[PDB]
Image: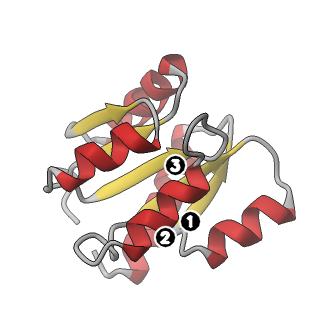
Amino acid sequence: ADKELKFLVVDDFSTMRRIVRNLLKELGFNNVEEAEDGVDALNKLQAGGYGFVISCWNMPNMDGLELLKTIRADGAMSALPVLMVIAEAKKENIIAAAQAGASGWVVKPFTAATLEEKLNKIFEKLGM
């Protein structure tokens, strides 16, 4: 979708969230809110209006996996783009992310170039 599309960045580390916010900014995406955990993310997403979720995998309370599943099972936001950020390239985590319906995944740390690439690749499919 347009770069006005509203992003939600989920991570229990504020420093990592500002990194993702800053990279999105650099790519031209200025509509960005943050969530400190899956619960805060879902409370916020139910508030409607978001067009893309970038979520950390490893998070306390509700990890990234649970968030993705709740979203994919939520009839109203089941189609919401979800990019998962993971700490290592472990096939376990990756395959489960794909299986749970992750629109894509990235290994942190990542560059603006990669984020752009993933974002473009996903916008591609969705034809956005």
Q: Return the residue at label 3.
A: 115
Q: Return the residue at label 2.
A: 121
Residue at 42 percent across and 82 percent down: it is: 125
**Gap in Å between the C-alphas at discs 2 and 3?**
10 Å
User: Can you say which quadrant of the picture contains the N terminus?
Assistant: bottom left
Whether label 1 touches label 2, CB < 8 Å: yes
Three-letter amino acid code at the position of disc 3: Leu
Question: Judging from the image, what secondary structure is the residue with disc 3 in?
Answer: helix
Whether label 2 touches label 3, CB < 8 Å: no
x, y percent for residue 59? 61, 37
x, y percent for residue 99? 65, 78
Is residue 117 visible in this depiction of the protein? Answer: no
Tell me if residue 110 comes above or below residue 66 in the rendering: above
Q: Farthest residue toward the front?
A: 61
Question: Judging from the image, what secondary structure is the residue with disc 2 in?
Answer: helix
Query: Badge 2: few (under 14), some or many (20 or more) residues near its Cα, within 10 Å?
Result: some
107 and 63: which is toward the camera: 63
